[PDB]
Length: 140
Image (cartoon, rainbow, N blue to C red; front, side):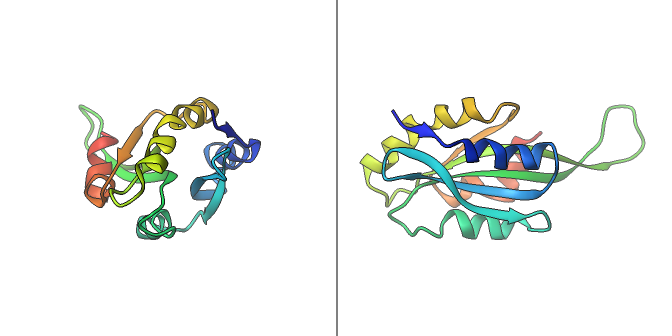
């Protein structure tokens, strides 16, 4: 079905390997290809990511990649330390047209095969599933 532009992979790798950015928002351009829409600078925080993934309005869907920071403590140790983990999310609000929602759903696997290494996936249809609390519970 839908292809993936090489720019999705290079932007992704600049985060994983070089820590150059904090997040990316992707979109399907003209029902043909997944492209980059927004690149968050490394110092960005999560609220901005959430405001960017919804910036297309209630008729739109998006994908998002975020290098999420949280606190973790390994068994038997005496301290808790900050960690970070990449996750890839699909965002399809209920107000979007079924056709658009289905296309973003069917094309999600094409994007995941392109971003080798991501270990955590989330499919949200409302903000309750994309909150810091929902994500932190997922990344554990």
